[PDB]
Structure formats: structure tokens, C-alpha cells
Image (tube, rainbow, N blue to C red; front, side):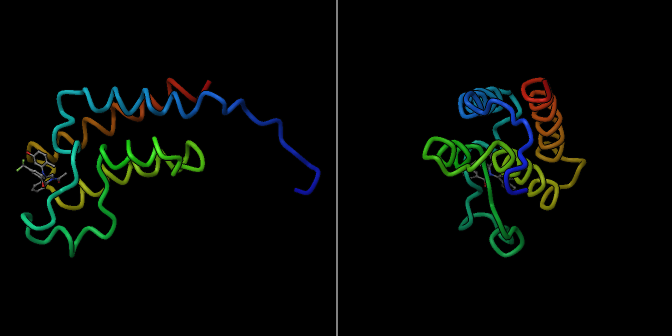
Length: 116
Ligand SMILES: CC(=O)n1cc(N(C(=O)c2cccc(C(F)(F)F)c2)c2cc(O)ccc2C)c2ccccc21
């Protein structure tokens, strides 16, 4: 509260660290469904059903232009990619499995990088 402040972590490297994690995501062989925005003109249903589309290239653009206030807002957008994927894809499909794999991959790197 006012004048009562928690000792707060050094957030100086967060921008660089998030960029590194995003690069690792993008180079994963199962990243291909997520590298570019879903084509809203070519995929029936997607625009109407998925209220907040997100993909790795859009996250990169947001990250590089100072549009994430903090690392938590970055994590939310990454998770949104996989939540959208779950909403629109059967678990028993290539993209369905890709989404599962990539979420697991992310969460470990997230834990390994930031939870001391
Ligand atoms: C995440 C997710 O659920 N999906 C992603 C899809 N997808 C496209 O919409 C897409 C976008 C641009 C070009 C191309 C193409 F070059 F392949 F034609 C495909 C996609 C497909 C790919 O093979 C590779 C990359 C992307 C972004 C997509 C398509 C249908 C249903 C869910 C989808």
C-alpha cells in the first residue's frame, strides 16, 4: 500500500529474457501452427469463434514495440495462443497435439527462467 513496498525483483532483464523464450518457442519444430496469424478470410468460423486471436509473430511485434507492461502480460498472450488452439482444435489432431506440446514447453522455460 502507500509507502509500504514489497522488496521487488530486478526486472531489468525481463524484456531480454522474454525475447529469448519467444525465440526458443519459434524454433521448436511444433511451432508451425502458431508462427503467423490464422487467416481469417480462409478459415471458416475462426473470426466469429475466436474473440482474441494471437500468434507468435504478433507477440514478437508487441514485445519489440513496448506493448507488454510486464512479464505477466507477456505470459498471458502466450497462453492465449494455446487457449485459442484448444478452443478450435480437437485434442486428437496434429495442431491439437502441437498446442499441448508447445504449452508444456513454454511453461517449463517460464518456470526455469523466472521462478528463481
Ligand atoms: C492455430 C490454429 O488453430 N490454426 C492455424 C492455422 N493456420 C492458418 O490459418 C494459416 C494462416 C496463413 C497461412 C496458412 C497456410 F500457409 F498454411 F496456408 C495457414 C496455419 C496452418 C499452417 O499449416 C501453418 C501456419 C498457420 C498459421 C489453422 C488453419 C485451420 C484451422 C486452425 C488453424
